[PDB]
Image: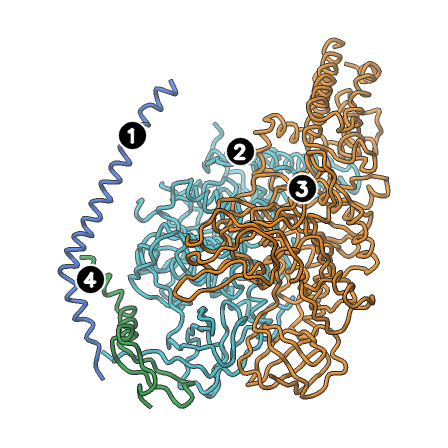
C-alpha cells in the first residue's frame, strides 16, 4: 500500500476577511480539503478551502474568523474531503451539527468512513416508489398519501404546530403491515431549532420508547451558521448508509428547512456570489437538489429512503424562493393552513393545495380500495367549488347559495368539521376514514358528480 | 507600536500589526480613538474606528489592546449609567466637568479607587476552588448584596484568601495556583460581549414573571427566563411596562438597554428612573437605581456602539445571573439596533438581503435572543438564576412584515401586543387581547395548577369568552343586541365587564397601581364563576340584569379594592362576594 | 540547525524528526506519535471489522 | 381492579430490568470474548502498525 504521510501544518496565513481565511505558499493544495485551524490561543476549529488558485488557498473557517492572528495561527491540511464516520452502531444516539456525540457517550467506532455529498444514483438503476406508509395521521394517508421512497415536505408558517405533527409522525411511524429489524429507522435532522424545541424533541423521542431506532442530528441556533449546512449532508449520508448498505428503510426528517435556506443565504452573501430571487444564491436549486434528490429506491438493494422535510413560509407566502424551489424539486406538498388553526383544529392540514405527485402509484389494488382515486379526486375538487360558493355568499349574501351552491357550502362545512379533524393520538385507518369521505362526497347528489363515475363508488357499499 | 497608513473615513489601515487578531479592539492615534479590527490582510491590519476619524495623522501611533470588545464587570456595576461601549457617563461628566463627551475619553468603566466592604466565605487558605465558585460576597449597597464569583476559565487549589475588611478593586483579593504557577485575581472580571457566559445546564423555565399588571399576569403570562416582545411605538406603554418591571417584577435586578432612540426620549427615561421608587415587602422604602443598571446609547453615539449596546446589556445580565439572581433585560428599540446594523453593513458593502438588511440579521437576532433562560449556575454552591429579555419592536406603521418584526415574532415565545387603538380609547394597560399570546402557558401550567387547579380552567374559559366577544361584536353590528339570546346577552355582558373591570387596569390609581396574583386569581374566579352560574339558568336576561345590580356592583368593585388590606383580607372579601353572587344567582333561579 | 538549542521532548515525542523551511512557516511534523495517530485513524474500520467475528 | 392489574407490573418491570442487566453482562462477556478477541487480535493490529517505511 502507498506509504502514509503526516499532514503539513502551515503558518503562512496571509489574510482574513469575513468568514474567509486566506493562505499563501501552500504546497499542493486540494479542492474542498478539510483543514482544521489552530489559533494562537490553542483552540481548534475546522474549515474548508473554498477557492484554490495557484499556490494560494481561500479557506472558510467554521467557528468564525474571530481570534485568528496573521502570525500565530496554524492550518493543517488533511488532504481529504469531509467524511462522516458512519456506522450501524450510530443508531439510538444524538449528535451535534458536525456529529460530535452529545449523549455523554463514547464516539462512533466507524464501520466505514463515507464522504458526504455522495454521488448520484445512476437513474437507469433508479426505481419507483411502490408502497404506502402508515405514519399514523388520517388526512395525510387518505389524500395525498406518502410512498415508501417518496419525498414530500410539510408547508407550515411560523407558530403553527408543525413541530408537534413531525414529532407525532416520528413516534407513530410504521409500515402498513398489510419485519422489526428492517422497520422504519428515522434520521431526524434539526437545522436551526430553538433550545426549548430541542429539549421537547429529546424528551418526546425518549418517551415513545423508539430511541432504539431513531437518530437525532441536532443543530441549535447557537451553533455556527456554516455548521448548519453540513448537518443535512451528514444526516442524509447516515441515512444512505443505513438504508442502502444495511437494508432498513429510513424515514428522513429535516425540520426548519427555511433555516437551511437562511444559512445558504448567509454563506453566499459572505462570499459575494451571484444572487437569485430575494438575494438567495443563484445555485440554491442545485443545493436543494443535493439535499432532497436522494429519496428513492435502488433496484439491487431492498432499502428505501423516504424524505419528509418541514419548510416554513417566511411571510406565509407560497411564492417565496425557498418553498417555490422546493415544490419544483420535492415531488408534492402537504400543506398546513393558519386559517384552519384559527378554527382550533389540531392538525391544520388544508387539502386544497396538498397533492402527492406519486399518489397515482401508491394507490392500487394491492392496498387501499378500488375507489380511492375517484373519492380523493372528488374530495379534492368539490372543496374548491365550496370555497367559491363561500366567496359568492360573502360578496352577495346568504340568498345567493341556490339549491346547488348551498349543498357545496354544507359539503365544505362538514369536510372541515369531521373529515380533517383527528385526535392527537388517533390512528384512523383508511377504510374507516374512507367511509366518512364517501359520506362527504354523498352529501352532494349521486348524479351531479361530474368527474367521478357512479359505478366506481357503487362497487363499494355502505355498511 | 503601529502606525496608520490610510484613513478613508471610518475605515483605517495600520501597518506593523502582524500579531493582531481579528475583532481585537485597538487604540488609534494620540486622541486614543477606539476601533475594531476587521481584516488582517498582509502584515497590515484594517480598523473601523467608532468615533469620528477627522484629524488623524499618517504615522500617528496605534496601540493594541489584546482583547476583543469586552466589559469590565464586578462591584459598582449597578446604579451607574453606561454608554454603548461601556463608558461611565456619570463619572466622565464629573471628571471633565463640561457636558460634551470628549473625543477619546479614557475613564475606566468602574472607579478602581473607591472602597467596598468585602468579606470572604468560610473557605480555607489551602482548599480547592474552581471556576464559578462563590468565594465572597460584597455589600455594594444596602439590600443589593453582591456575590463575588471566581471567574470562569480559572481554577486551582487555594493559596491566599483576603480576610474581611475594606478594599478596592485594585487590591489583589485572591491568589491561587493550579499548577506550580500561581495567579492572583482581583475583584474585576473582563468578558467579551460576543461570547456568552459559561453555563452548566439550561433549565426549563418554571416560574412566571409577575409584572404586577393583571392583563400580563393572567391573560398572557410570561415565565422567568423567557423572551418577550412589545410593539412599542406610541402610547407610553413601553415606559409603563418598563416602570412596572423595575418596581414590582420578581426580578432581583433590571438592566435597561437603550440603543439609537431619540436623545430627549432617553433623557426623559433616564430622569424617570431615579424618580421611580419601590417599597420593600418588609415595609422598607428603597430606590430602584440601587438594583437598576442602565445602558443608553442615543442616536448621536457611534453606530458601532449602538450595535454593541445590546450585547453589552445581555452580558451584564448574564454576569448578574452568574450568582443566581433573577435579572430582566429590556431592549428599548430593537428596530434602532437593526437600523444600526444595516448602516454598519452598508459601510462594509455586504451584499444586501430582503428589504436591505444584511442576510445575517435574523441569525444574529436569534443568537442574541437565545441567551435568555433559567440556567443552573456554574460552580458551587448550588444555586440557579434566570435572564429574561422583554425586548420591544417598532414595526414600520404597525405592519408586522419587516424582517426585524418577522424574525422577532419567529423567535420570541410571548408577544404582548400593545395596541394604539386601545390607547385612543383611553385604555391604561393598552394590551390588545385579540393579538397577544403566551406560548409558555403549557410549561407554566404546572405552577398554574399547583397554585390553583381551577385557575387554568378559568383562563381557558376567559379565552373562550374573549373569542366569543368579537362574535357578539359583529352580531350586534349586523342585526343589533335584539337578536341576542338570554345566554348570548349574558355572555356579552360578562365579556364587557371583564374588559372594563379586570382585563383593564387603572395604573395611576393607588388601589390599582399593583395587582397581586392573588387578587387577580380571585377576581378571575369571581367573574368566571358568576358568568357560568348566570349562564346555566337560561331565565330572562332583563330580569337577571335587574336583580344582579348588587352582584354587578360587587364584581366591578372586586378590582377597586386596594392592596392595603393584604392577601388574607382581600381574598376573604372576594370569596364572600363570590359566595353572595352564587347565592343570588341560584336562589333567584 | 539541529536540536542544538531546543529539542523534541523525549517521553512526549517517542522519536522521529520535524522538518520545516526557513522561518518555520511550513512544518512537516513527521514524528512517530503523529504517524501512529494517523495510521490508527485510517485503519480503525479494519480494527472494528476484525474485532467482530 | 386497577391496583391488582398494576401489581404484576411491579414484578414484570423488575424482571425485565434484571434480564437487561444479564444481557448487558453477557454482551460485555462477548467483549470479554472481545477481550479474548483482544487476546487474538492485539498482536495482529500491533504488527499492522509496521507502517514505518520510506
Q: Secondary structure at mark 3?
A: strand
| Residue drawn at the location 84% of the way across and 30% of the way down | B479
Q: In the rendered image, which quarter is residue A115 located in?
A: bottom left
Q: Position of residue B400 (x, y in %)?
A: 72, 53
Within-10-Å neighbours for mark 3: few <14, some 14–19, many 20+: some
Chain ID at mark 2: A
Give how far apart the Cα atoms at labels 1 and 4 are.
Answer: 38 Å
Q: Residue furthest top?
A: B587
Chain identifier for the orange-coloured part of the image: B
Q: Mark 2 touching mark 4, by CB under 8 A? A: no
Shade representing chain A: cyan
> Can you tell which mark lies on residue B437?
3
Q: Secondary structure at mark 1?
A: helix
Give how far apart the Cα atoms at labels 3 and 1 are.
Answer: 45 Å
Which residue, given by chain and number where applicable, does mark 2 sit on?
A: A436
Give how far apart the Cα atoms at labels 3 and 2 are.
Answer: 35 Å
Which residue, given by chain and number where applicable, does mark 4 sit on?
A: C50
Callouts 3 and 1 in the same chain: no
Please state which of residues B452 and A191 is positioned toward the viewer in this rendering.
B452
Chain identifier for the blue-coloured part of the image: D
Viewer-nearest of discs 2 and 4 = 4
Shade representing chain C: green
Which residue, given by chain and number where applicable, does mark 1 sit on?
A: D12
Give how far apart the Cα atoms at labels 1 and 2 are.
Answer: 42 Å
Q: Position of residue B502 (x, y in %)?
A: 76, 31
Work out whether C34 lies above or below D24: below
Give how far apart the Cα atoms at labels 4 and 3 are.
Answer: 59 Å
Q: Position of residue B398 (x, y in %)?
A: 77, 52
Viewer-nearest of discs 1 and 2 = 1
Viewer-nearest of discs 3 and 2 = 3
Amino acid at each position: 500500500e502507498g506509504t502514509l504521510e503526516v499532514a503539513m501544518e502551515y503558518r503562512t496565513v496571509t489574510g482574513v476577511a469575513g468568514p474567509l481565511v486566506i493562505l499563501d505558499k501552500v504546497k499542493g493544495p486540494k479542492y474542498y480539503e478539510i483543514v482544521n485551524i489552530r489559533l494562537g490561543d490553542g483552540t481548534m476549529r475546522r474549515g474548508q478551502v473554498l477557492e484554490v488558485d495557484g499556490e494560494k488557498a481561500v479557506v472558510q473557517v467554521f467557528e468564525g474568523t474571530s481570534g485568528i492572528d496573521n502570525k500565530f495561527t496554524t492550518v493543517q491540511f488533511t488532504g481529504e474531503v469531509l467524511k462522516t464516520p458512519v456506522s450501524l452502531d450510530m443508531l439510538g444516539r444524538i449528535f451535534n451539527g458536525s456529529g460530535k456525540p452529545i449523549d455523554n457517550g463514547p464516539p462512533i467506532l466507524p464501520e466505514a468512513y463515507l464522504d458526504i455529498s455522495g454521488s448520484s444514483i445512476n437513474p437507469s438503476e433508479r426505481t419507483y416508489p411502490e408502497e404506502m406508509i402508515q405514519t399514523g395521521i388520517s388526512t395525510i394517508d387518505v389524500m395525498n398519501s406518502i410512498a415508501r421512497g417518496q419525498k414530500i415536505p410539510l408547508f407550515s408558517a411560523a407558530g403553527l404546530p408543525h413541530n408537534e405533527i413531525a414529532a407525532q409522525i416520528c413516534r407513530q411511524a410504521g409500515l402498513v403491515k398489510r419485519g422489526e429489524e428492517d422497520n422504519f429507522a428515522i434520521v431526524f435532522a434539526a437545522m436551526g431549532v430553538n433550545m426549548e424545541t430541542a429539549q421537547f424533541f429529546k424528551r418526546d423521542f425518549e418517551e415513545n420508547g423508539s430511541m432504539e431506532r431513531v437518530t437525532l442530528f441536532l443543530n441549535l441556533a447557537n451553533d455556527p451558521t456554516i455548521e448548519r449546512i453540513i448537518t443535512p449532508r451528514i444526516a442524509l449520508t447516515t441515512a444512505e448508509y443505513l438504508a442502502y448498505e444495511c437494508g432498513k428503510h429510513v424515514l428522513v426528517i429535516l425540520t426548519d428547512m427555511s433555516s437551511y435556506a437562511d444559512a445558504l443565504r448567509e454563506v453566499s452573501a459572505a462570499r459575494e456570489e451571484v444572487p437569485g430571487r430575494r438575494g438567495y444564491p443563484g445555485y440554491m436549486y442545485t443545493d436543494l437538489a443535493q439535499i432532497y434528490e436522494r429519496a428513492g429506491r435502488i433496484e439491487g438493494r431492498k432499502g428505501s429512503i423516504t424524505q419528509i422535510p418541514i419548510l416554513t413560509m417566511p411571510n406565509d407566502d407560497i411564492t417565496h424562493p425557498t418553498p417555490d424551489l422546493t415544490g419544483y424539486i420535492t415531488e408534492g406538498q402537504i400543506y398546513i393552513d393558519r386559517q384552519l388553526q384559527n378554527r382550533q383544529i389540531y392538525p391544520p392540514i388544508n387539502v386544497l393545495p396538498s397533492l402527492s405527485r406519486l399518489m397515482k402509484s401508491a394507490i392500487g389494488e394491492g392496498m387501499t380500495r378500488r375507489d380511492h382515486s375517484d373519492v380523493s379526486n372528488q374530495l379534492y375538487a368539490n372543496y374548491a367549488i365550496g370555497k367559491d360558493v363561500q366567496a359568492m355568499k360573502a360578496v352577495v349574501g346568504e340568498e345567493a347559495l341556490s339549491s346547488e351552491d348551498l349543498l357545496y357550502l354544507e359539503f365544505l362545512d362538514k369536510f372541515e368539521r369531521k373529515f380533517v379533524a383527528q385526535g392527537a393520538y388517533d390512528s384512523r385507518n383508511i377504510f374507516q376514514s374512507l367511509d366518512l369521505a364517501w359520506t362527504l362526497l354523498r352529501i352532494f347528489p349521486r348524479e351531479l358528480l361530474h368527474r367521478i363515475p357512479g359505478k366506481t363508488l357503487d362497487q363499494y357499499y355502505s355498511r | 507600536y503601529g502606525y496608520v497608513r490610510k484613513v478613508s473615513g471610518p475605515v483605517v489601515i495600520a501597518d506593523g500589526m502582524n500579531g493582531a487578531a481579528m475583532y481585537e479592539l485597538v487604540r488609534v492615534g494620540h486622541d486614543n480613538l477606539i476601533g475594531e479590527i476587521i481584516r488582517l490582510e498582509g502584515d497590515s491590519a484594517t480598523i473601523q474606528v467608532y468615533e469620528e476619524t477627522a484629524g488623524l495623522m499618517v504615522n500617528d501611533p496605534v496601540l493594541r489592546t489584546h482583547k476583543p470588545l469586552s466589559v469590565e464587570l464586578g462591584p459598582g456595576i449597578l446604579g451607574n449609567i453606561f454608554d454603548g461601549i461601556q463608558r461611565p457617563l456619570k463619572t466622565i461628566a464629573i471628571r471633565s466637568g463640561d457636558v460634551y463627551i470628549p473625543r477619546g475619553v479614557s475613564v475606566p468603566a468602574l472607579d478602581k479607587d473607591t472602597l467596598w466592604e468585602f468579606q470572604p466565605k468560610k473557605i480555607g487558605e489551602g482548599d480547592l476552588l474552581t471556576g464559578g465558585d462563590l468565594y465572597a460576597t460584597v455589600f455594594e449597597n444596602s439590600l443589593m448584596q453582591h456575590h463575588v464569583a471566581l471567574p470562569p476559565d480559572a481554577m486551582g487549589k487555594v493559596t491566599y484568601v483576603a480576610p474581611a475588611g475594606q478594599y478596592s478593586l485594585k487590591d489583589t483579593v485572591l491568589e491561587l495556583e493550579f499548577q506550580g504557577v500561581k495567579k492572583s485575581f482581583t475583584m474585576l472580571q473582563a468578558w467579551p460581549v460576543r461570547t456568552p457566559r459559561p453555563v452548566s445546564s439550561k433549565l426549563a423555565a418554571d416560574t412566571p414573571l409577575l409584572t404586577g399588571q393583571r392583563v400580563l399576569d393572567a391573560l398572557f403570562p410570561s415565565v422567568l427566563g423567557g423572551t418577550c416582545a412589545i410593539p412599542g411605538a406610541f402610547g407610553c406603554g413601553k415606559t409603563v411596562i418598563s416602570q412596572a418591571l423595575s418596581k414590582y417584577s420578581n426580578s432581583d435586578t433590571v438592566v435597561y438597554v437603550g440603543c439609537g432612540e431619540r436623545g430627549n426620549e432617553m433623557a426623559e427615561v433616564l430622569m424617570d428612573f431615579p424618580q421611580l421608587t419601590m417599597t420593600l415587602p418588609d415595609g422598607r422604602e428603597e430606590s430602584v437605581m440601587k438594583r437598576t443598571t442602565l445602558v443608553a446609547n442615543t442616536s448621536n453615539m457611534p453606530v458601532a456602539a449602538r450595535e454593541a449596546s445590546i450585547y453589552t446589556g445581555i452580558t451584564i445580565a448574564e454576569y448578574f445571573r452568574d450568582m443566581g439572581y433573577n435579572v430582566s433585560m429590556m431592549a428599548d428599540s430593537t428596530s434602532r439596533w437593526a437600523e444600526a446594523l444595516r448602516e454598519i453593513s452598508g459601510r462594509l458593502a455586504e451584499m444586501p438581503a430582503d428589504s436591505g438588511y444584511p442576510a445575517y440579521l435574523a441569525a444574529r437576532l436569534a443568537s442574541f435572543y437565545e441567551r435568555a433562560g433559567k440556567v443552573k449556575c456554574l460552580g458551587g454552591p448550588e444555586r440557579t438564576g434566570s435572564v429574561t429579555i422583554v425586548g420591544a419592536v417598532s414595526p414600520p406603521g404597525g405592519d408586522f412584515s419587516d424582517p426585524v418584526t418577522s424574525a422577532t415574532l419567529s423567535i420570541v415565545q410571548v408577544f404582548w401586543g400593545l395596541d394604539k387603538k386601545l390607547a385612543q380609547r383611553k385604555h391604561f394597560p393598552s394590551v390588545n387581547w385579540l393579538i397577544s399570546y403566551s406560548k409558555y402557558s403549557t410549561a407554566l401550567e404546572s405552577f398554574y395548577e399547583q397554585f390553583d387547579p381551577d385557575f387554568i380552567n378559568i383562563r381557558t374559559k376567559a379565552r373562550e369568552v374573549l373569542q366569543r366577544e368579537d362574535d357578539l361584536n359583529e352580531i350586534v353590528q349586523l342585526v343589533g343586541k335584539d337578536a341576542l339570546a338570554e345566554g348570548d346577552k349574558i355572555t356579552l355582558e360578562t365579556a364587557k365587564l371583564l374588559r372594563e373591570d379586570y382585563l383593564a387596569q387603572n395604573a395611576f390609581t393607588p388601589y390599582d397601581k399593583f395587582c397581586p396574583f392573588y387578587k387577580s386569581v380571585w377576581m378571575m374566579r369571581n367573574i368566571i364563576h358568576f358568568y357560568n352560574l348566570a349562564n346555566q339558568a337560561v331565565i330572562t336576561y332583563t330580569l337577571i340584569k335587574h336583580r344582579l345590580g348588587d352582584l354587578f356592583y360587587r364584581l366591578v368593585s372586586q378590582k377597586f379594592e386596594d392592596p392595603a388590606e393584604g392577601e388574607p383580607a382581600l381574598v376573604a372579601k372576594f370569596k364572600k362576594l363570590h359566595e353572595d353572587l352564587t347565592a343570588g344567582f341560584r336562589a333567584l333561579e | 540547525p539541529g536540536p542544538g538549542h531546543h529539542n523534541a521532548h523525549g517521553p512526549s515525542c517517542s522519536g522521529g524528526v520535524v522538518v520545516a523551511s526557513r522561518d518555520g512557516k511550513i512544518v512537516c511534523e513527521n514524528t512517530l506519535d503523529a504517524r501512529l495517530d494517523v495510521v490508527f485513524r485510517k485503519k480503525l474500520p479494519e480494527i472494528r471489522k476484525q474485532l467482530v467475528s | 381492579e386497577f391496583q391488582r392489574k398494576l401489581a404484576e407490573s411491579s414484578g414484570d418491570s423488575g424482571a425485565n430490568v434484571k434480564r437487561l442487566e444479564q444481557e448487558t453482562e453477557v454482551k460485555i462477556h462477548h467483549l470479554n470474548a472481545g477481550a479474548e478477541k483482544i487476546q487474538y487480535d492485539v498482536v495482529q493490529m500491533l504488527l499492522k502498525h509496521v507502517t514505518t517505511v520510506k
